[PDB]
Length: 173
Length: 177
Length: 64
Length: 64
Ligand SMILES: *CCC1=C(C)C(=O)N/C1=C\c1[nH]c(/C=C2\N=C(C[C@H]3NC(=O)C([C@H](*)C)=C3C)C(C)=C2CCC(=O)O)c(CCC(=O)O)c1C
Ligand SMILES: *CCC1=C(C)C(=O)N/C1=C\c1[nH]c(/C=C2\N=C(C[C@H]3NC(=O)C([C@H](*)C)=C3C)C(C)=C2CCC(=O)O)c(CCC(=O)O)c1C
Ligand SMILES: *[C@@H](C)[C@H]1/C(=C/C2=NC(=C\c3[nH]c(C[C@H]4NC(=O)C(C=C)=C4C)c(C)c3CCC(=O)O)/C(CCC(=O)O)=C2C)NC(=O)[C@@H]1C
Ligand SMILES: *[C@@H](C)[C@H]1/C(=C/C2=NC(=C\c3[nH]c(C[C@H]4NC(=O)C(C=C)=C4C)c(C)c3CCC(=O)O)/C(CCC(=O)O)=C2C)NC(=O)[C@@H]1C
Ligand SMILES: *[C@@H](C)[C@H]1/C(=C/C2=NC(=C\c3[nH]c(C[C@H]4NC(=O)C(C=C)=C4C)c(C)c3CCC(=O)O)/C(CCC(=O)O)=C2C)NC(=O)[C@@H]1C
Ligand SMILES: *[C@@H](C)[C@H]1/C(=C/C2=NC(=C\c3[nH]c(C[C@H]4NC(=O)C(C=C)=C4C)c(C)c3CCC(=O)O)/C(CCC(=O)O)=C2C)NC(=O)[C@@H]1C
Ligand SMILES: *[C@H](C)[C@H]1/C(=C/C2=NC(=C\c3[nH]c(C[C@H]4NC(=O)C(C=C)=C4C)c(C)c3CCC(=O)O)/C(CCC(=O)O)=C2C)NC(=O)[C@@H]1C
Ligand SMILES: *[C@H](C)[C@H]1/C(=C/C2=NC(=C\c3[nH]c(C[C@H]4NC(=O)C(C=C)=C4C)c(C)c3CCC(=O)O)/C(CCC(=O)O)=C2C)NC(=O)[C@@H]1C
Image (cartoon, rainbow over all chains, first blue to last red; front, side, top):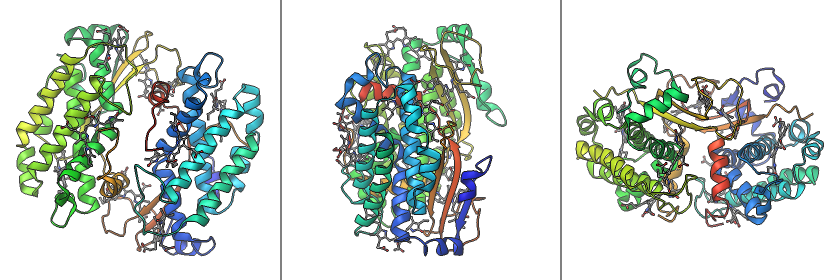
């Protein structure tokens, strides 16, 4: 899928059939891996909104004047960024590596946030809730909704996706 | 009644039409409680997915035979078709509330719908319960009786608009009974 | 008549009194922040949501 | 480099082993029911969701 990342229109690429069978032989736990990716993207809205909501409820000064997500414009920008990050993490889990996340999402991002005054403590908490939420889904610890997968253990993939979130946290700290 | 969007309903492609500014100010005079009515329509459409999914889920949890073999929403295809229909219905109700009448709902959504469902074996008891839950959910939003999400409106009374939208749901229920 | 084509009126309500404007989005006339948009679109099947309801219907949500 | 264009990989995962097929959706070779699609899309601002989070952030949801 690398050409999707670098193409000018980002038009969709599709892999199925034998190409997808082959791809599932280069990464670990290919079927659980696709269920894990599916769990992230299928729930992207609620993951993002629960995570940004929690960063605010733990620090409501963030929606007061001078606050990081004061006004709808800034709240919407923050929700957008949380989704962007989440999606780069989903693509890292699909591909089994973080090179695109680091190159296209993280490189220069802390500098951008420092220039804008986007608060690092708030970003840290949004990322830690997104991580906890995704790991919760992948390990059957989500309480309202469960995944439609065969029952089993996905702890290795939870550790792997946790590491991708940790790369975000580390870069933005 | 507000007729500005009539041409959207009848056009070949359904391309969007828009009204703002002084045109919209004048349009709102042709329906009661224009501002609260836009807020009510916004509450429906902004929450369309959760309204539909909570309503179909309740249908099923009260009558789980609906997802067993020979059931109305057995297989993902049937469940998806039912969630789609619930959204279609909710959207025609939202347009009824925007325009202050149910003529388009009756003509383009309800006229023929009972007979179609009879031909397909879509159970009436299940449709009745999805509709009554959607009605309750929408009324709950409009009357500050939603627990997980509150609206961002000025505080006040919207009981007349809740009664009006309840009537539009009742037309659906009556047509599909 | 119900035309069996899945097409339904999609109403969108805008309140941009906060002055936050997106490029390319002025489609009617006005500067008070309000707009109503209606289109007629085919409502699609959502396999992902159908899977979730089939799995999760027995869980009470939203304090219902 | 982060390009400041809001574009992110949009991944979509398909499992159509139940045999339900939608017209015109075959976009790659394959007959076992599985497909992954990836596109690069600008992630949009969502004013309605921003409004909701501003109002509702203090409501615990989803048994958290
Ligand atoms: C859109 C989701 C939502 C948010 C967000 C919110 O704040 N309220 C929301 C939904 C909502 N639901 C209802 C009412 C009902 N929902 C159900 C379905 C669930 N009940 C079950 O037994 C079940 C299976 C286990 C469900 C799934 C039902 C039955 C109702 C009651 C319908 C009735 O006849 O009155 C409301 C209305 C307010 C309320 O709490 O009742 C709302 C706002
Ligand atoms: C995507 C929505 C969702 C469904 C559906 C589901 O079943 N679970 C879901 C989300 C989810 N959230 C968490 C964990 C947390 N959520 C929050 C924010 C809320 N807590 C607040 O105090 C607050 C303001 C009042 C909220 C909004 C937080 C803080 C967490 C914990 C994060 C942590 O560091 O552990 C999960 C993970 C499992 C769990 O229930 O804890 C999930 C799946
Ligand atoms: C943690 C992720 C989950 C969990 C996931 C499991 N999935 C298992 C088997 C499995 N899943 C799929 C579908 C998947 N593969 C694809 O190619 C695509 C689409 C591109 C998807 C959505 C398949 C085909 C399989 C193999 C079994 C089958 O044919 O259905 C699984 C069993 C163990 C294993 O096969 O590795 C598990 C445990 N299960 C959980 O309880 C957590 C929440
Ligand atoms: C039940 C529906 C709600 C409730 C709604 C109220 N809205 C009130 C006033 C109001 N709302 C708007 C925005 C609306 N008008 C538009 O044209 C559009 C977009 C096209 C929108 C979204 C305006 C401009 C106003 C009037 C200014 C004001 O009073 O703030 C309102 C006050 C009573 C009234 O004006 O008739 C109410 C009660 N309030 C609730 O508590 C429930 C949940
Ligand atoms: C039957 C009505 C089902 C239903 C199926 C749908 N699939 C939709 C989009 C879609 N499905 C695939 C996977 C398929 N195409 C392939 O090339 C391969 C393997 C080689 C398979 C397994 C793809 C790639 C797509 C997207 C096509 C595109 O990118 O243009 C779909 C449309 C969703 C929409 O219109 O928004 C449907 C309705 N959906 C259901 O709910 C029932 C259970
Ligand atoms: C600033 C970044 C805001 C934000 C604004 C957005 N508005 C979006 C779409 C949109 N807004 C209107 C209303 C506007 N157009 C008019 O003609 C009039 C009155 C005459 C007004 C008040 C419309 C009609 C539209 C749709 C445009 C169309 O149908 O082509 C929008 C795009 C969302 C998307 O692309 O998916 C944005 C970002 N959004 C935010 O979160 C901050 C608070
Ligand atoms: C949410 C958890 C945060 C929060 C986020 C904000 N980001 C704001 C502006 C902004 N964000 C980016 C990075 C974004 N663009 C990309 O292209 C990619 C990856 C490919 C990402 C992750 C940029 C470049 C910008 C400015 C330019 C633009 O929006 O196009 C923002 C507005 C800040 C301001 O204007 O002062 C916010 C509020 N803010 C918070 O407080 C929490 C911690
Ligand atoms: C959900 C609460 C129900 C349920 C709904 C089902 N409807 C099914 C097929 C279907 N629905 C319609 C009406 C729909 N199409 C429109 O154009 C309009 C309004 C403009 C509406 C409201 C049609 C025409 C059809 C058949 C053709 C099609 O889908 O394009 C359906 C599949 C039935 C089957 O194949 O056996 C279901 C499951 N089913 C339930 O059990 C609950 C009560």
